[PDB]
Amino acid sequence: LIAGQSARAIMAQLPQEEKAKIAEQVEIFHQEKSKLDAEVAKWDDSGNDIIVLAKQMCMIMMEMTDFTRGKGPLKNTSDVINAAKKIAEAGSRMDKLARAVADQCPDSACKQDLLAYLQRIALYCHQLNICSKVKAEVQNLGGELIVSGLDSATSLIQAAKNLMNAVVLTVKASYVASTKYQKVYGTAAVNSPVVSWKMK
Image 1 (cartoon, one colour):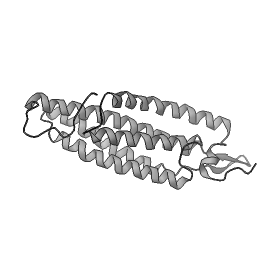
Image 2 (cartoon, one colour):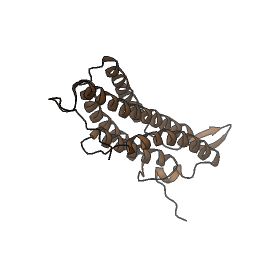
Image 3 (cartoon, one colour):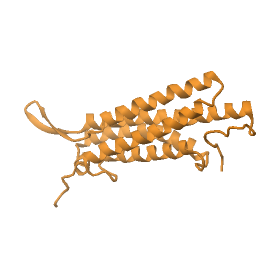
Image 4 (cartoon, helix red, strand yellow):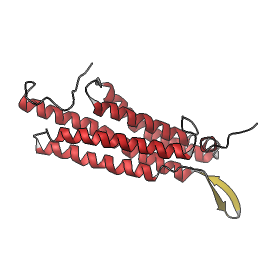
């Protein structure tokens, strides 16, 4: 018929071999995403923006990886680039909250883990941006022109997985830091905790 010429449509018709390798890599990302599904389900995001943000970031990352399989709401490469900017704004906001939480944390070692994770978020947000220009491209394989999108895809996906892991680790670790605050100063502490960890 009259096939689409959009970037998304093109990714959808990559050579089978490459679609296979991309699925392998998407799976690995999916595994790291379920750990986030698991941890995020525990709680009720009212009064906890860290959780909301983590959900937003998860969602936008799903769109980005879907793009590489030729699916999802992102049509053009510029949409993927924009998606990556959204994630970075989100990640920056979270950074403001989690940093507040560590500034309540009185257990200097618990403060540690949250801070180190926070900089992984900055780092992989960044690398996600750098890797966001995903596009099939023309290549020359021994005098034969082919179309490949594998490397561009896998680069994005890896950055997405790495980011996901850092988000999970940041959600967990900021929870732990919140408890260490409550354990020490009790629910009747004058300064209420930065985020509320309700269980619903």
